[PDB]
Length: 77
Length: 59
Length: 30
Length: 65
Ligand SMILES: [Ca+2]
Ligand SMILES: [Ca+2]
Ligand SMILES: [Ca+2]
Ligand SMILES: [Ca+2]
Image (cartoon, rainbow over all chains, first blue to last red):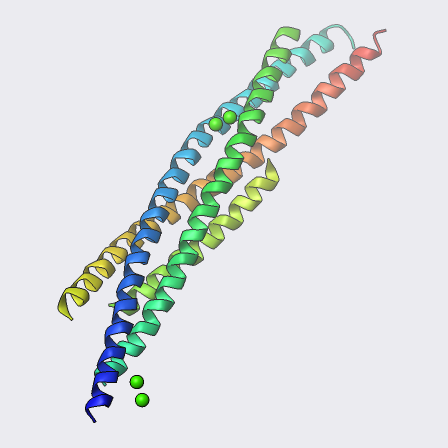
């Protein structure tokens, strides 16, 4: 009977020790996720502004092609 | 029953670690993905800025 | 309290999977 | 034992709080990407429209020769 109780306790202990080690690993995995997540938001913010510049640049081209077309209309071509 | 609740608690800890790990892997994939696209957008921004200059000089 | 975490994490997972799908789409547009 | 249980409890409390931030970050991410995807769609459209008008202007011009 003493052997059985001791075996159970030692199993509880060791299973609990592994659950602790798991929570420690959880902690590294969420910390790193946060950093990746933050990095992603910064890159997206930078790229947001880059896409704004590109769109503006497509609008620029657009208006100059209206100048080119008005010139062609004026020259009968 | 004390051991019993440790045993089932343990299983759920492991289940929770698996999800967290999956979540971490997505957050890493996302950042790689967005970083990569950072570089495709650099070239597009460059190609566009020069097309702007071209069209402007030609008109 | 353990249970509230498992479900909380699986929600973010679902959200990050949709997000990653949009970015594979954004990868295709570039 | 109680130093192990207490640590396991602080760890999980801490993971949880951080899961809450990750959710908030994932949602903002999703929104910013939806907005940039629409913007990319207007860029593609405008680039193709720009290229048609470029090709057309040139073709009209090539008749001048
Ligand atoms: Ca035995
Ligand atoms: Ca034994
Ligand atoms: Ca860049
Ligand atoms: Ca670069």
